[PDB]
Length: 111
Image (cartoon, rainbow, N blue to C red; front, top):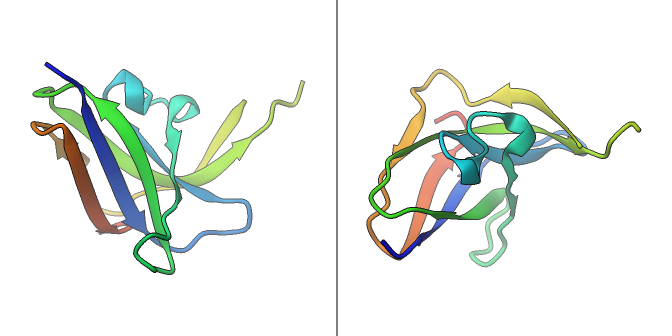
């Protein structure tokens, strides 16, 4: 099974110093531990105002559950990931990647 490159996208507002992050049920997504979550980056290639994206390599045919959160990625006091808010009243998101390249546009944060 030759790996699947998945672009996960979500839109929303953020506080100063805050970013969007993806966390989930496999290594690449940090095994539900926000400390090992993946921070998204702003996506400007479509001319949107509030779009964020993360490109993640996942194993083909393996089901993965995930959620977005908004939080802070800080430097050590002596790393620190602080979740402000996990996505709103909705079931954890899921994907079973089958293609080599996939774009998952999850719309608006919390929806």
